[PDB]
Image (cartoon, rainbow, N blue to C red; front, side, top):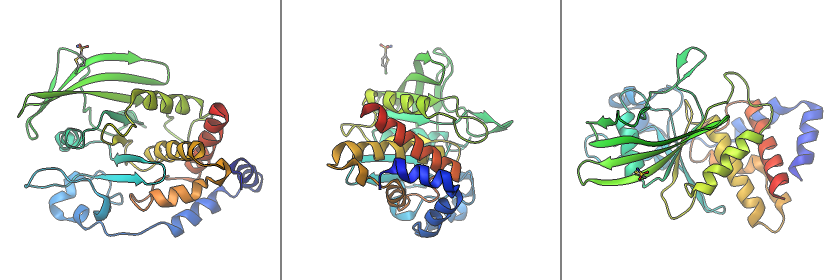
Amino acid sequence: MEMEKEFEQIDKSGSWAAIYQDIRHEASDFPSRVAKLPKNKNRNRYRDVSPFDHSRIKLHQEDNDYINASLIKMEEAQRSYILTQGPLPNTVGHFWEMVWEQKSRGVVMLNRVMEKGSLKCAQYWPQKEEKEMIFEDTNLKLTLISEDIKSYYTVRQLELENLTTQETREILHFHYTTWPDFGVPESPASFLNFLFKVRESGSLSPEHGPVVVHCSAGIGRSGTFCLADTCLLLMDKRKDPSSVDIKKVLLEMRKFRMGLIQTADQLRFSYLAVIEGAKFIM
Ligand SMILES: NS(=O)(=O)c1ccc(Cl)s1
């Protein structure tokens, strides 16, 4: 069923809440035993958001390999994403270790450091060229190289140096800065513009490791980003784009990380972004 028609049918009936709860009811449940170990309690921002053991990213150290991050592997679309929480004060060095080990080209950030008067994630990147950051626990150095500030997003060029080997890489930081404190954007136009800027960078392409995507918990806004990207990709690859079922794509993605898409408004916004995205590159 064409999703544009499904959309109008749900909207006229006002059944967004009932669709969303059907997804929650059918979603996968897998063990998260590593996330719940007592040694990892300060590595988790939220007690009810954990990575599944089967899909978690492992850090390459013998001490403690744990980070709140999951590999989402979409077999038919041929895309991979790492979804993670906003870094904590004691996990900033783990975060950049993961970026290094997984060979990511891009970091996608969908939240502000402060929202609703509370801290949603640590200030994990340098704000001035001449004041670099050193993460002593993971032996990495991070330098701001360039800054391009637009109305809806900022793009930063960063230099990450493995102080052990003195190799350096260029990491692109894509920061979406205008998601509202409550609800979802009214129009998906600026979110779709942002997605096509990430695509054009090469950050989503198979010659790099997976893109690292985060918001505060790494399930809501982060979920919307990878659901829209994957749905638009399959609509271009398939002989019938009307065969793309966004609810089935979301349940496939929820096999790899719990809770992706946090509200019925985020589910409706996802339909909108895909509906408009397709209708712009049509
Ligand atoms: N300073 S620059 O030549 O623009 C530069 C680009 C990429 C880096 Cl990493 S450093």
